[PDB]
Amino acid sequence: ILQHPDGTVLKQLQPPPRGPRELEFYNMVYAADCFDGVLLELRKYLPKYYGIWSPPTAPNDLYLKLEDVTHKFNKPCIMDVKIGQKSYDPFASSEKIQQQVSKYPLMEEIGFLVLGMRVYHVHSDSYETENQHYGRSLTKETIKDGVSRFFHNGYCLRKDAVAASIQKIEKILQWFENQKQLNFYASSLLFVYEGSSGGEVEVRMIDFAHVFPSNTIDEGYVYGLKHLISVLRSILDN
Ligand SMILES: COc1ccc(-c2cc(=O)c3c(O)cc(O)cc3o2)cc1O
Image (cartoon, rainbow, N blue to C red):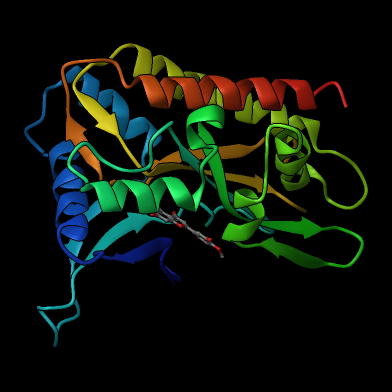
C-alpha cells in the first residue's frame, strides 16, 4: 500500500493467482455498464476504484488505484480486521488449508481476526501500533479487550467511534443478508476514526484476492460481522 498525496493509494497486485483475481473483482464491481443492484449497492462499502495503474516506464508492474479512505482524517486511527470463519478459499490444497488454519486456529470459533492497528494517543501526540501477532494472540477470553484497545486514546474509551462502527457495519451486514452471488475469503474491514469530529468513522471492505461466485449466503462472513457487532456492543458498557 503506497499512499499518494492526491488522496489515493496504489495497491500492488499480489502474485498470481491472487492479484489477477483482485483486479477482476474490482473490474466486475465497478464495470461502467453494470446495472446489477447488488453490485451497485456494494460500491458504497468499498474504496472508490480508479482502474488499473502501472508506472509509465513499467507496464509489467501492476497496481490498483484506490481511494485512500484515511485521507480526510487529521490523525487517523486505523484497524484492519479479517472477516469470516475460513481464511482459505474453496480451491485450496489440503496443505494450504492447514497452513491457513494454523495461522489462526480460532477463526471458525471467533469469525474475525485483527490484522493490525495504529492508534493515536492524545497525551503523547504519538501512535501505538500492533502487528499481526497481536490479533493472532487473542482468544475468546481476551477478544473484547483486544478490540477495545483500538478505541482507547490513552485518556478515554471512544464509545462514539465504537457506536458509529456498529452502525456502519450494520449496513454492510444488511448487504450480505441481501445477496447470494459472492462469497468472500480472507477479506477485511478497514476501520478508521479521527484521533484528534465525534462519531465520524469509516468502515470499508478491502482485500479481494479470494472472492468467488456463489449460489448461497456468505455464512462465515455473516457470522463474523454478527460476532464483531456483539463484541463492539459489549464495549459500549465498559
Ligand atoms: C498508515 O497506515 C495506513 C494508511 C492507509 C491504509 C489504507 C487505506 C486505503 O484506503 C486502503 C484501501 O483502499 C485498500 C486497501 O487494500 C488498503 C488500504 O489501506 C492502510 C494503512 O495501514
